[PDB]
Length: 103
Ligand SMILES: [Cl-]
Ligand SMILES: [Zn+2]
Image (cartoon, rainbow, N blue to C red; front, top):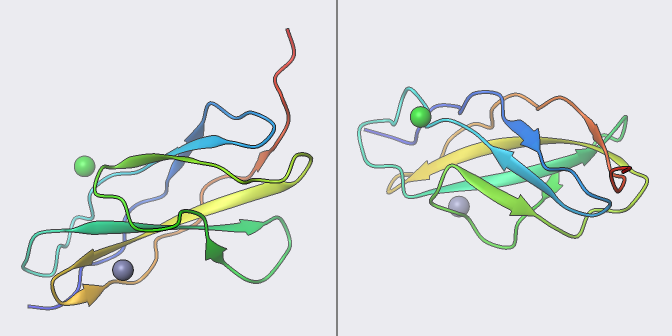
C-alpha cells in the first residue's frame, strides 16, 4: 500500500480574466488507502515549470483557481495524496486563455 496513481485529465471552466474552475475525477488507483487531498499545478503555455496553483491541497474534486495573470495562457494538472504521500501528476488539461468573457 503506497501513494495513489495519477488522476485523469482535468477540465477547466468558468474562465475569467484572472480565475478559473478546475475539476477532475478520483484516481482509479488509490494505492490502497483513502485519498486525503489533491495538489493542483499550473504551467503557462510553452513554459517548462509546473507551479502550485492553490496554496494548500483541496479534498473536493474541483477548485476555483485564482491569481492567474490576465492575458496569459495556462494548463493545469492534478496529483492525489493519501496517508503514504503524493502520487504522480496526471496529464495536463487543455490550455485556456485568461480573458474576461465578452457580452
Ligand atoms: Cl470520480
Ligand atoms: Zn501534499
